[PDB]
Amino acid sequence: RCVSAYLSRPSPFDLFIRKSPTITCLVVDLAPSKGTVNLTWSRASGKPVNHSTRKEEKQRNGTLTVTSTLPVGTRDWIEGETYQCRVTHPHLPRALMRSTTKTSGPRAAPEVYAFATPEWPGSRDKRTLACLIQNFMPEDISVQWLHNEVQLPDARHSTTQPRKTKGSGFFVFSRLEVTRAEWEQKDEFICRAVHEAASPSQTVQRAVSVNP
Amino acid sequence: PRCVSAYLSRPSPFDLFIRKSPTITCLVVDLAPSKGTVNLTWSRASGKPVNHSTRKEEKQRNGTLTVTSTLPVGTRDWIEGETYQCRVTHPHLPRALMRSTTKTSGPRAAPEVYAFATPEWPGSRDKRTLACLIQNFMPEDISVQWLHNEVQLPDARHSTTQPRKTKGSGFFVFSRLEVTRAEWEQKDEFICRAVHEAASPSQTVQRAVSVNP
Ligand SMILES: *[C@@H]1O[C@H](CO)[C@@H](O[C@@H]2O[C@H](CO)[C@@H](O[C@@H]3O[C@H](CO[C@H]4O[C@H](CO)[C@@H](O)[C@H](O)[C@@H]4O)[C@@H](O)[C@H](O[C@H]4O[C@H](CO)[C@@H](O)[C@H](O)[C@@H]4O)[C@@H]3O)[C@H](O)[C@H]2NC(C)=O)[C@H](O)[C@H]1NC(C)=O
Ligand SMILES: *[C@@H]1O[C@H](CO)[C@@H](O[C@@H]2O[C@H](CO)[C@@H](O[C@@H]3O[C@H](CO[C@H]4O[C@H](CO)[C@@H](O)[C@H](O)[C@@H]4O)[C@@H](O)[C@H](O[C@H]4O[C@H](CO)[C@@H](O)[C@H](O)[C@@H]4O)[C@@H]3O)[C@H](O)[C@H]2NC(C)=O)[C@H](O)[C@H]1NC(C)=O
């Protein structure tokens, strides 16, 4: 058992689309009822942080997981503010510190390719849609699926973690199982990516149907 | 902080079924270099003898010492459900570390393999990307390879995802293979092959694909 902490950047969707970005500090592998863990937010500039939301949940594995989500200013983030999570506990050797700021370096917009699986024996009342988004940088990307131009619940699909392409960019796969009911009432699906380098409006999408 | 952790892998279905020379690997991460040596000890639950293992040490560009032991195992022994344990002996560790591994057991289900070529995208048109979705297999142990002209490419040429749960009972995986004009022009024949215990016969399922059919 080893307590670790993870500090996330805002989702490009939250940041560019909803324009209400948040960051999250995730603390894993805590021993329940060993008193409470303090999660403290701060800014490198020293300016005030918003009220954060804290979530605790005991895990099937006897772990305690704690998260704090902090809303951040769109301007502040995009302008390069640095945000720190500090994790405290009297029962804990040192204190834990993660920090986060907008990514740097060169940008490159995503290529988005969407594919339908051919009918495979057995369940023919199901197909799988898949999406390859690649050659973007930096690695921060949001993926979503739409049916009939309306966004599906995020739980409907699986998206992979950004892996390095053989070059300088990253790629990602998204998988979306669909039903006959769905593609029959309209065979229109969109894999949409949100990425800082996509112009304009940080969005790139690709349509795909079960039939060609 | 810094957490020494240990990982014990099952044999690759390729090694196991195709090369019929399976191995397991114990990986120990986040060691403090020159804190003396870490012992990695192999054992079998049946108490029968273990082969000679290979040990690899490498300081990482992050200051971490990484240690691995690879143990060759009997095909029969594995498939018959022998259990193998890695024991990790070290000073900076209060409790010794123990991982164990055995063949998986539960519902079997063969993989569905679908292969796709990316359309020509502006910029580099001397490159395409092949992609493969393998899904609905169980258990999660799978090998993926790409062939061009019926000959297997170097594993480094492609990226394969980690098995994720499908919405159902099975797993899926994606493989990505960038190709060159030189390659698909001299023959536009590529195969995504999976090796999986549930695939019959001969534990193999593959699918062909080409740049602009
Ligand atoms: C008890 O059981 C729980 C699960 O039920 C385990 O909790 C998990 O713990 C692991 C590791 O300790 C966590 O892994 C880390 O997750 C981070 C975020 O998770 C996802 O969700 C966010 C959005 O909330 C996404 O941004 C992200 O893509 C993930 O989908 C990752 O960011 C971590 O980083 C990984 O990639 C980076 C590359 O930048 C590497 O640096 C890291 O090394 C790593 O590869 C990492 O994946 C996991 O999040 C926890 N699950 C939950 C609840 O989300 C406990 O670990 C378990 N305890 C024991 C003893 O087993
Ligand atoms: C300092 O730098 C080193 C060197 O890069 C980092 O070491 C890596 O650390 C991670 C996590 O500790 C190791 O992850 C483990 O890899 C195992 C083997 O992976 C290889 O083989 C598999 C086949 O199983 C391939 O699919 C894969 O692409 C690799 O080729 C996996 O078996 C493990 O998977 C299990 O645990 C992870 C936990 O993250 C889960 O997400 C999985 O679902 C699964 O349960 C595991 O991922 C990695 O191998 C190390 N690299 C090596 C080989 O040295 C240090 O992490 C880094 N320290 C810092 C600063 O973070």
Image (tube, coloured by chain):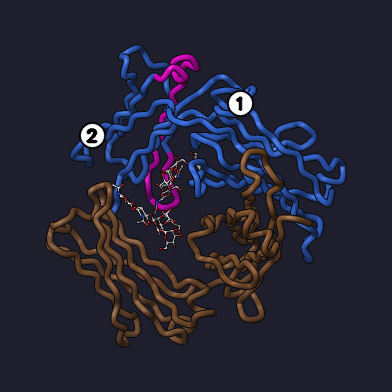
Chain colours: A brown, B blue
Ligand 2 under 8 Å from disc 1 Cβ? no
As measured in the structure, the alpha-carbon distance from the residue carrying label 2 to the one carrying label 1 is 37 Å
Circle 2 marks a residue in which chain?
B
Q: Residue at x 49, y 28 (%)?
A: B11
Q: Which residue is mark 1?
A: B203
Q: Position of residue B143 (x, y in %)?
A: 58, 34
Q: Residue at x 85, y 40 (%)?
A: B187
The reply to whether the magenta stretch includes residue A44 is: no
Residue B143 numbered tag: none
Residue B202 % position (x, y): 63, 22
Mark earlier in primary sequence (2, 1): 2
Disc 2: which residue: B96
Residue occupying image coordinates x 47% and y 16% = B74
In the rendered image, is residue A49 in sight? yes
Magenta-tinted stretch: B58-81
In front of the other: B176 or B2: B176
Amino acid type, residue under disc 1 in the picture = Gln
Secondary element under disc 1, as helix, strand or loop, is loop
Residue at disc 2, secondary structure: loop
The answer to which quarter of the image holds residue A30 is bottom left
> Which residue lies at the image location 34% right of the left edge and 46% below the top edge?
B30
Of badges 2 and 1, the one in the foreground is 1
- Mark 2 is surrounded, within 10 Å at the Cα level, by few (under 14), some (14 to 19) or many (20 or more) other residues, namely few
Amino acid, disc 2 = Ala
